[PDB]
Amino acid sequence: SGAIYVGNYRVVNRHLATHNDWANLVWEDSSRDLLVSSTTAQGCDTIARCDCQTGVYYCSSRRKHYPVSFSKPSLIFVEASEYYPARYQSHLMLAVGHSEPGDCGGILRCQHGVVGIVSTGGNGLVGFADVRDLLWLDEE
Ligand SMILES: [Zn+2]
């Protein structure tokens, strides 16, 4: 589990979005596993605006933050998980590291702020849904 709180936006994995998120929907994309909902309260998270490929992510299943190198956001084939079939996922960054389904929502951060959230796992890789291209999260 986990979310990004930027301005009046809540960013979550689409597969973990609640009824309240859908009832306050701003934007969603299945291919990216992202959904954004509107919030009453101001969030303080800063979204990274950068092309960093090193950062730190939170792994709930190990109660640890791990420094990682990660690929640039790409269209990648993802094997079946407990929450998605085998399919292509877009805007996905991969690192070597641990990721269980419950780790989805863990933040990946670089010196510039929040890069993305854990979205995929398996075969000793962790995949992150990038948010750094969603420049509109910074405004409205
Ligand atoms: Zn950065």
Image (cartoon, helix red, strand yellow):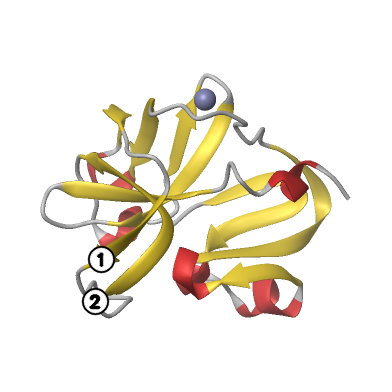
Seen at 63% across and 36% down, the residue is 47
Nearer-the-camera pick, 68 or 106: 68
Q: Quadrant of residue 96?
A: top left
Query: At which x and y percent is residue 79?
Result: 19, 69
Relative to 98, say whether 21 is above or below: below
Relative to 14, say whether 76 is above or below: above
Assign the N terminus to one quadrant of the image.
bottom left
* Mark closest to the chain's N terminus, 2 or 1: 1
State the SS at label 1.
strand
Nearer-the-camera pick, 131 or 118: 131
Seen at 50% across and 30% down, the residue is 51
Nearer-the-camera pick, 2 or 67: 67
Instruction: Measure the C-alpha gap from mark 2 to mark 1.
Output: 6 Å
Please name the residue that numbered disc 1 is placed on: 78
Relative to 9, say whether 42 is above or below: above
Q: Residue furthest top?
A: 111
Query: At which x and y percent is residue 105?
Result: 45, 53
Task: Give the label on residue 86, or none.
Answer: 2
Q: How crowded is mark 2: few (under 14 residues within 10 Å), some or many (20 or more)?
A: few
Seen at 59% across and 31% down, the residue is 48
Asked whether, in this view, residue 25 is left or right of residue 92, the answer is: right
Q: Which residue lies furthest to the front in this view?
A: 75
Q: What residue type is labelled 1?
A: Val
Asked whether, in this view, residue 102 is left or right of residue 32, the answer is: left
Q: What residue type is labelled 2?
A: Ala
Q: How crowded is mark 1: few (under 14 residues within 10 Å), some or many (20 or more)?
A: some
Task: Give the label on residue 4, or none.
Answer: none
Mark 2 and mark 1 in contact? Answer it, CB < 8 Å. yes
Seen at 77% across and 41% down, the residue is 138
